[PDB]
Amino acid sequence: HHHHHHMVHITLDRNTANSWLIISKDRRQVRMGDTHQNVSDNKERFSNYPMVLGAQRFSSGKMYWEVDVTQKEAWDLGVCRDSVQRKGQFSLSPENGFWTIWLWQDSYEAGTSPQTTLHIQVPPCQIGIFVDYEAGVVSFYNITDHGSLIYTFSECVFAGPLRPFFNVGFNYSGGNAAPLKLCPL
Ligand SMILES: Cc1nc2[nH]c(C(C)C)cc(=O)n2n1
Ligand SMILES: Cc1nc2[nH]c(C(C)C)cc(=O)n2n1
Image (tube, rainbow, N blue to C red; front, side, top):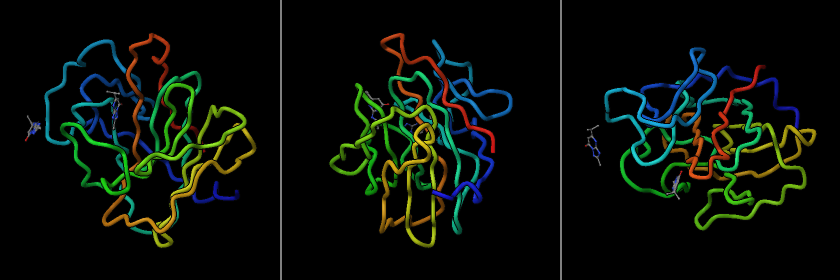
């Protein structure tokens, strides 16, 4: 790809975070805490899963950012509608307002309904996310493998403003404590 030059500075929105998440001072890293993080509840917080949104809202143009996933066992990344459900159980799908990929149990999958198997030869340590609002495209790139394409959602029906979307995953195994980190431009 050659999408780096639509690079945007993403920061995480504390107010949307699940109450067990710990967001760094610079709002560029997030990890799972070992307990509730002593915050009040609010209607924006994802209740059931270790999810958080970016602060930025996009309704036009081309946007690109990169996320470090080094030594994690489980995570979800992509974009979602500003109006996605926050409370209770739900699946990650375009019908529910999400355009995501994930790692789970040694397999990478795209969040279609039902999910799509991804074919990645070089396990990624950093993921690039490209959104073309006007074209209705969300694409995922393997920065560890010279920027190779992972997956493209096309004909997307955004139906509203978009926000960067993150899930650090649970840490039942003790092997998934590592943070998600927004990489420098
Ligand atoms: C399922 C569900 N969880 C909540 N939590 C709250 C606040 C206490 C944040 C309002 C609300 O309507 N719901 N609905
Ligand atoms: C949408 C979604 N569904 C789940 N389910 C679980 C476990 C209960 C399997 C963790 C998680 O992060 N998510 N995110």
